[PDB]
Length: 463
Ligand code: HEM
Ligand SMILES: Clc1ccc(-c2cnc[nH]2)cc1
Ligand SMILES: Clc1ccc(-c2cnc[nH]2)cc1
Ligand SMILES: Clc1ccc(-c2cnc[nH]2)cc1
Image (cartoon, rainbow, N blue to C red; front, side):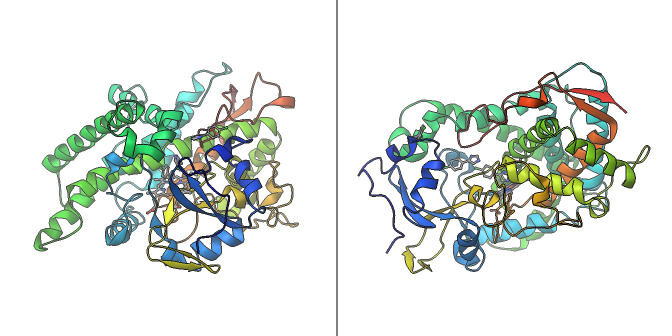
């Protein structure tokens, strides 16, 4: 009944079958041979694998409700412990997500605005960037400090100075925590947590960092409830917290302490590594195609220019910018395996039958590179999102944020985040790196199922 695949080893499953090349080309091969949606047994864990725009969509969109449930990710779970909105299933999920959305958009007025807030951080990014002035520098950390700062602003209410002792001792972790989750002993744990639960090692060390972050969060929440002003709701914490008051009249409501605290935690968990990486890779790309950055730099001017602040109402009158912004995302393909779904009920897909909770990885990477929707699917080439008359050409296969009932909660936030950060830099300061444009290597340093670009250095020559 389950979709077809490679016969597993009875204990490891196919984890041996992977190593052969990349742990994703391994998948490529195990398409027909086996087709477009197959199963693989990771460890002892049966996993369906939607592969390729059409197959992904058909399931995740046209059967969206069935496929909308969140899969197991056992390593970081012992903490997230099934709360908050990445990681909830059930009504809890359909309700926290409902909250979280209403609470942006109607985050404006005020103040501030997510927009104003990103610009505020941008002013700062530029400001901090000007200081080096020709002097080359790995901007992989200020990209992590600017991405992370935004989330702070939203959840905590204010942005930290980069130099800040808490912020730093918090940014590390996050990124180390990330680093650890993406290590061999984590991957093993992910699959055999049942066994390795009981013995020490990086799965604990991971949870201890996250625990720390929580005690900060929970701490900040008191401070928030003390200072709490029902009239001026400072941020997410506040707004939740006041909504929480509202629910005092319900014997059994769903907005309890730990859905707040862990959500806050999750927001960070989502809103940092990825959106920073995409910027790193963004600038790195701009370097290898120094003219694409030029073509944008001219467009930057025509529509904005010398003085004012770059505004969201720009991208609409700037196709290339956004086109580029898309190709940066398509190409860099930063979540390649998507984040685990599982089906809510037994479910009928393409004739096969997946029992309740059968896990399913939407292999989007297969969609950002889908040969059916793009041509030189493997090269960086913005004309992937242009047409002949060089206006935007959106594509049903571009889904870096996933697709359907689950699509990335902070998609908007990031979509904007990229745009401004990208334009507000490229407004001020022209990329120039020691590394020769001829052969910049877009190879990632490593994957750990999370490519990060080979570490790099460029200068920022102003105006
Ligand atoms: C370009 C950078 C980003 C990418 C590529 C990205 C991508 C994704 C993807 C692919 C998913 C999986 C949806 C699924 O399969 O269930 C997701 C989920 C999620 N992401 Fe993002 N994301 C980005 C930035 C952010 C930011 C900035 C935030 C916070 C502001 C965020 C918050 C979330 C949340 C809360 C979920 C859980 C959705 C749910 O199941 O309710 N992400 N993201
Ligand atoms: Cl090249 C390669 C390396 C490691 C794995 C792996 C991770 N977890 C189990 N096996 C697979 C393929
Ligand atoms: Cl385990 C996990 C889940 C979701 C994300 C994410 C969503 N949006 C951006 N990053 C990252 C890591
Ligand atoms: Cl099985 C599995 C799937 C996805 C991840 C991931 C994606 N982004 C960060 N971590 C980790 C482990």
